[PDB]
Image 1 (cartoon, rainbow, N blue to C red):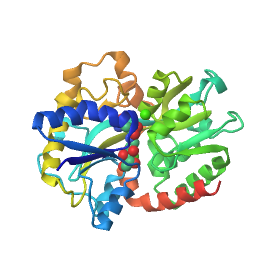
Image 2: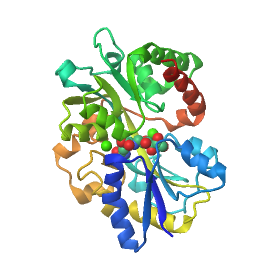
Image 3: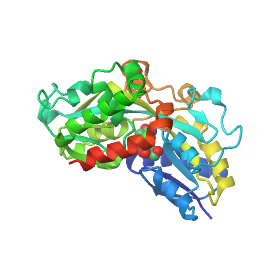
Length: 325
Ligand SMILES: NC(=O)CC[C@H](NC[C@@H](O)[C@@H](O)[C@H](O)[C@H](O)CO)C(=O)O
Ligand SMILES: [Ca+2]
Ligand SMILES: [Ca+2]
């Protein structure tokens, strides 16, 4: 009888549960069960099997087009949110944004001190910065990182990846780096643990996971330079067993009154513009936020239109880079 909600575990899932799920479910007087997953294809497997157990799934904005095309997502009720309260394009007919985050470069201060990599060109430069690299085992942010390393200006990432030539060169760049990649991390918590144990010299991972590891004593530093500004959000699984209750739950948790608490401990940025007026975050708090003006200036936004067209190519080609060893 519980609504089943799933995200990717660790500090991020804990932040959503504390700020959004527990207070929203209390207000609606409903019960819910949590689950965890890393790949949107796991939601597809539930749909393909004919046994859907998940109701709400937290996915990345760039997985939304391929999930919707594969018939994995329920169409949401018309006025689930007022689109004017959220960033443009962050709310689709099948997805409601809950946050902005960054896929960024972090480095081990024991290895490099303050003179760590401060750009993707630096991250890919094994001669100037020798050491163990860690990259995600999924391609969003990883293909673009290679395009940036090749010298592509931040505002031209997706123009470069719009051609076959550019897409192949980006994979060739990742192939070149692959022998220096000690671990292809799978979850944010695993990435945070690699950082806390100093098991890697540099890593491309999510800002909240990095800041959480540093708060826990990791001797790492990071930059927003060349980071990808992402958007996470919620969708309802096609054939969700508690579809109607899940719709009410998603509408409630998207409210400004809950969104304001999302970054209380975890370094994330709420997507609901009204949450900023309620919480009145200090400039120190804003500095860790992916969407703060000073951080946006050195980032580029993920392009869901690119991922709508090339996700299948990207998944297979990147699988081969990591399988090359
Ligand atoms: N929004 C945030 O502050 C969290 C950022 C980050 N979330 C990564 C997600 O895009 C990712 O796990 C996707 O949900 C997943 O691949 C399926 O779409 C994290 O798990 O630390
Ligand atoms: Ca994502
Ligand atoms: Ca974590």
